Length: 129
Image (cartoon, rainbow, N blue to C red):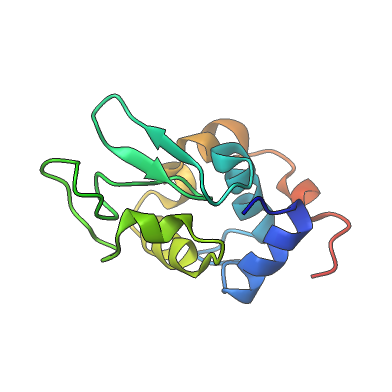
């Protein structure tokens, strides 16, 4: 599923991401834009053999099981396929664990490089929340 901007903002809010660990909704929408272009089915293979999955490009090295990342963990206790669903519940739950892990949203490289310190409220402007 490819979400629209305001449609994703609403879905994230419903699932309790707005202001989670102090990050406003705009940060989450911004990170989703540049990680996946709002596509729940997005996947990307890394040079180390791990794969990033879903709307927030959650990585198999630590967070989910895909059966093909040797020596990896599955700290969200889910198959990586669950992160590709049209329903974003699994991705949001895992993102909450990730952002609590110590480095905040810096865990998302695209957020650090393209969202951090910018006018992220622009991403929720005009949206009926």
